[PDB]
Amino acid sequence: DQTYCDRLVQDTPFLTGHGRLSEQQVDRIILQLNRYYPQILTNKEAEKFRNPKASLRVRLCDLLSHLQRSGERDCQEFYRALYIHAQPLHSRLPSRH
Image 1 (cartoon, helix red, strand yellow):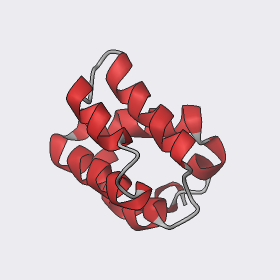
Image 2 (cartoon, one colour):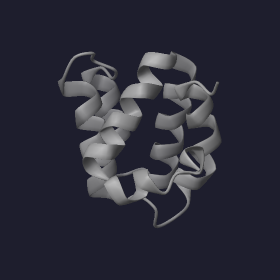
Image 3 (spheres, one colour):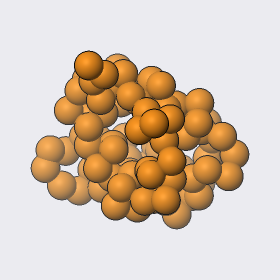
Image 4 (cartoon, rainbow, N blue to C red):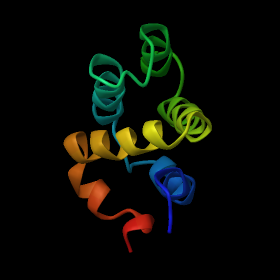
């Protein structure tokens, strides 16, 4: 009976571990969430989460917190984007097993 946002809360510590996602993967995930329908992130949000000056882990933490707070649609789309751009990691998520 887990919702997509339940899954995301469950998966967040795993997803944010160093090495798990690369900058290229996180950047493409952000683009995926901004460039299509539904538009999960605004352009300004997308720029903030891609900002090369902040550590990837901090940006990723902040993105996942943002999606958790934004509801089921946003959490679901994150999982679709993760499948597209980081499939091996997507297959290993705690919430799958």
